[PDB]
Amino acid sequence: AVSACALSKCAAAANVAAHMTHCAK
Ligand SMILES: [Zn+2]
Image 1 (cartoon, protein in one colour):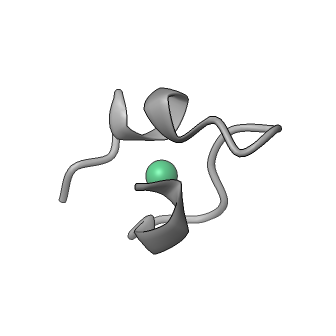
Image 2: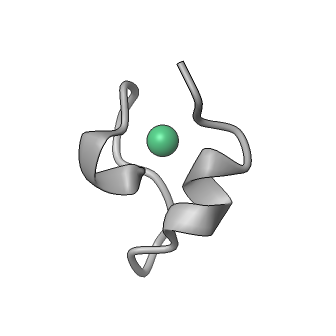
């Protein structure tokens, strides 16, 4: 979840899916 993203800010419009697509650690 972009809200709990481990790395810097993801997506350019709260696109969590775009984030989790590559963020899961
Ligand atoms: Zn992320």
